[PDB]
Amino acid sequence: GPRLRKGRMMDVKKCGIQDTNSKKQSDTHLEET
Image (cartoon, rainbow, N blue to C red; front, side, top):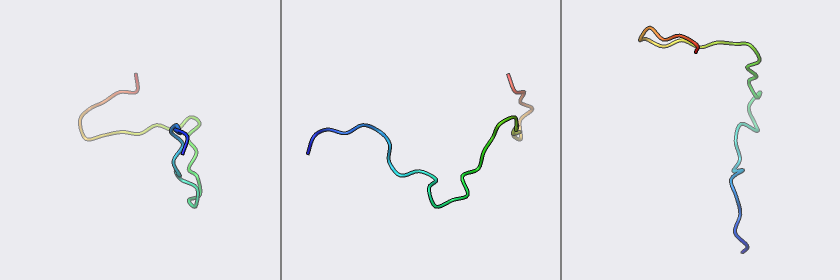
């Protein structure tokens, strides 16, 4: 009934991947800031 805000179910049944100091790359030559 009362309006709600974001918070829909997300990765809950998954292992919950954690990225502390990890980095990702793409096809185009991209740099991490």
